[PDB]
Length: 164
Ligand SMILES: CNc1nc(Cl)nc2c1ncn2CC1CCCCC1
Image (cartoon, rainbow, N blue to C red; front, side):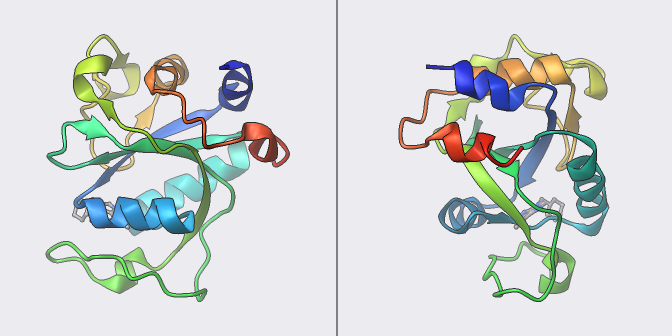
């Protein structure tokens, strides 16, 4: 069902994560971690303290799709087990240094064609697929976007709920 999902998304905040490659999203799915540039790192740390759930919605550049969504379970932390991110051009490991822990809610894809009816008030009401890495998605748009993803029956939201 979708009832526990709706509960997790209640009063949540939503951010679009744009990854330059599939490898880092796969690593994030395997390890439950994400790192972003310092500007977005600061925003996400602020958001984590402000809301019951902060949801990252992932999209790989040029894929035409979202690859799933996850809930922040921590603020960023430095000095843990290093993450072997594939670094884009001009990108260094220092600027990906803070690691957030995340719990995946959905690891399934959603093509942009299915979200064409959703616009984001915080990005000039452009289609929600449009946005730079870190763009915040307004509550109603973000909730409806997450509800469009195919259910991920491999995930049990019970433990996620027991962290809010
Ligand atoms: C593990 N984190 C990331 N991995 C990858 Cl491949 N791309 C990312 C990541 N965070 C943001 N982006 C997109 C930006 C776009 C501007 C230039 C630098 C990259």
